[PDB]
Image (cartoon, rainbow, N blue to C red):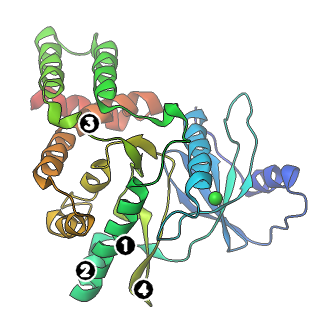
Amino acid sequence: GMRTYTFDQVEKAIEQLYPDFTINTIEISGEGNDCIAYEINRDFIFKFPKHSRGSTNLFNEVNILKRIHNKLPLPIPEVVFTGMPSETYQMSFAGFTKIKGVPLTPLLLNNLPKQSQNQAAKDLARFLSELHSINISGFKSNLVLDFREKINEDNKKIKKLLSRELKGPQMKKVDDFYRDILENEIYFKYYPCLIHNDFSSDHILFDTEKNTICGIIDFGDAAISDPDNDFISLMEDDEEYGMEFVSKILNHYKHKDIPTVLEKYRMKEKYWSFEKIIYGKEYGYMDWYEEGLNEIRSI
Ligand SMILES: [Cl-]
């Protein structure tokens, strides 16, 4: 079950741990699948978890940000307030400094003058180059997300989930899809590093007076995994920036195997149907689950 909050309960939660912090203004600033976010005093964003899974992502975000706060070339959220663990949440809330700016939507990017588009690609490449070069020696080993392990896990999850839903031959071809990707070593041979892992246009903030990127946000999915993940998340022509712009990022990053990035993107496009089934059933999102179930049913 998901949780809702009133403004009064948000204030009461903060006041229990921060009695000297006066709240003058509060409004909802956004809502995602994991947290509801509140703009408080017009200078802070407080995230409150909608469920236990979302609180684990929030706890991860807080811990990662504290490890990397002064290591990057763009502003990232700074943790200023933290809640506490309970039997229900790893972290009851967290409060971050607000970064002023708007998302660098594909529409906003493509209306920019070319010189500013090029600066945006360069700034993103430097951000990712520095992120992926952060020394990960100290980091907790459970942050490592091995992609081959993940694909094997999902295959077992899908069999468990769909054993009574799919007809025998349908499940056989699900098993075939998994077998084929697991035999292709290009997806699983990478050098692990710290990655953002949700590196998309909605998480890139832009200063429209300077026409420059002024922040990267929402680090709750960060992990030690394949650096190519942070390029393929920007490659979709519909919802993101497309291949031409991402190729500019790849050049400034000095990527040496662009064909492999493309092959990984192609497979992730196909793999989304299975992710929608998994996280559809997990979150209570039957919309997604039925959508993924119909997609794998036909193609
Ligand atoms: Cl921080």
SS for dot 2: helix
Residue 77 percent location from the top left of the image: 58, 63
Q: Which numbered circle lies on residue 208?
A: 4
Three-letter code for the amino acid on which mark 3 is drawn: Glu
Q: Is residue 164 above or below residue 191?
A: above
Mark 4 or mark 3: name the one nearer the start of the chain.
Answer: 4
Label 1 SS: loop
User: Residue at label 2?
Assistant: 118
Q: Of the residues under marks 4 and 2, which one precedes in the sequence?
A: 2
> In percent of the image, x 11 and y 24: which residue is there?
180
Q: Secondary structure at mark 4?
A: loop
Cα gap from disc 1 to disc 3, whole angstroms: 28 Å
Q: Which residue is mark 3?
A: 291
The Cα–Cα distance between marks 4 and 2, rounded to whole angstroms, is 15 Å
Q: Mark 4 Cα within 10 Å, few/some/many (few <14, many 20+)?
A: some
Give the amino acid type for the residue marked by disc 1 in the picture. Leu
Q: Residues within 10 Å of mark 3 (few under 14, many from 20)?
A: some
CA distance separating discs 2 and 3 = 37 Å
Whether residue 113 appears in this view of the structure is no
Q: CA distance from mark 1 to mark 2?
A: 14 Å
Residue at 29% from the left image edge and 21% from the top image edge: 152
Q: Is residue 201 left or right of residue 57?
A: left
Q: Nearer the viewer, mark 1 or mark 3?
A: 1
Residue type (three-letter) at the residue carrying disc 2: Asn
